Image (cartoon, rainbow, N blue to C red):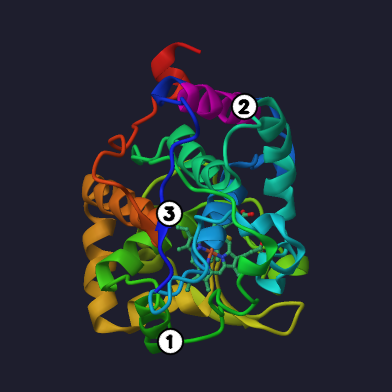
Amino acid sequence: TLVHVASVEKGRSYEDFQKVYNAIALKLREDDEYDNYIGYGPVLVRLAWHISGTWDKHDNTGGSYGGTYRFKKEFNDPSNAGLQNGFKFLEPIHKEFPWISSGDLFSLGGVTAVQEMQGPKIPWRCGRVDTPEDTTPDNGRLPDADKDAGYVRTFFQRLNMNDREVVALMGAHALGKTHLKNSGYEGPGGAANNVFTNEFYLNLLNEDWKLEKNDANNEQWDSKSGYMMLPTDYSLIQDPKYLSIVKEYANDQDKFFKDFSKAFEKLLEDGITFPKDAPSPFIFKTLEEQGL
Ligand code: HEM
Ligand SMILES: Cc1ccc(N)c[n+]1C
């Protein structure tokens, strides 16, 4: 019912946002030690997802538009524990480019992270506008990890995502790790990765998974190679419809990249009305492509 119309930051164009992208990317390169040398890429992807994943298609509450993660109710959501690291990373970027909206910054952080981690290009649109503290969605809109495929499927209908979009998005769980103090899940340690590939799907299909209890007394799936999956991750191979799609992405890197790009852009744009004369989506060059 609420309408959020994208409004381009005054006078700004592609080159302005490429500069912001570049600053994020240069800081990703510089701050390499974070989380035992994983770096900030994975947490920035999770931040972009969590600021977007509060959306409810029924009333257009939540979503990335309003930048409401900057308000304490949302930044203190138990579901967001650990994301303060990503926010702190983005603070000096926002100070350098104070003209960018909070939603644009948080979402751009995720795009930049995916691309700099050698993921697909993610087209990105500007024009999110900060909204007041009373527009902050209540806690409890982000998903639980201890549930089954039916829970996941129903959960993602609220975000207008179908089976293929859900399975594609979940491939982000190749990135980074779980931290017991944040979520009650732990790992991987030495098997953690900061390069974007389709390995989530290959690992689901090819590892010898054991259902174990962690030190927080929660169940998770662990392999002898040191990989781990949440119950919701493992549900993608328990449900026959999800399983077919897992097999598809395990066997086609390009298809996975293309589907993830579309689903991730969609996620980041849910709730936003783009005027018919809005700029086209921007596709930012990586530092590597720029020789930087
Ligand atoms: C059923 C849906 C999902 C559930 C239950 C879930 C749950 C979790 C949990 C519990 C963690 C660990 C947090 C921590 O301990 O630091 C995590 C991490 C992560 N999630 Fe998800 N997630 C879901 C979907 C997604 C989606 C759609 C994306 C993005 C496309 C995403 C991206 C990430 C990333 C990149 C990390 C690693 C963060 C880091 O290394 O600091 N997740 N997720
Ligand atoms: C939920 C999650 C996040 C990161 C990684 N690497 C694995 N999993 C299962």
Residue picked out by circle 3: 268
Cβ of mark 3 under 8 Å from ligand 1: the answer is no
Dot 3 or dot 1, earlier in sequence:
1
Element class at badge 3 = helix
Mark 1–mark 2 distance (CA, rounded to whole Å): 37 Å
Residue type at numbered disc 2: Arg
- Residue 39 position within the rendered picture, expressed as x and y whole percent measured from the top left: 65, 39
Q: Residues within 10 Å of mark 1 (few under 14, many from 20)?
A: some
Residue at position x 47%, y 69% in the image:
55
Label 1 near ligand 1 (CB < 8 Å): yes
Tell me what residue is drawn at x 49 percent, y 23 percent.
Answer: 16
For label 1, the residue is 151
Mark 3 residue type: Leu
In the picture of the structure, the residue carrying the numbered disc 2 is 29
Between residue 55 and residue 156, name the one nearer to us: 55
For the record, the magenta segment spans: 16-29
Q: Name which residue lies at 42% across and 14% down.
A: 290
Drawn side of residue 94 relative to residue 125, left or right: right
Instruction: Tell me whether the residue at label 3 lies in contact with that at label 2, contact meaning CB atoms closer than 8 angstroms.
Output: no
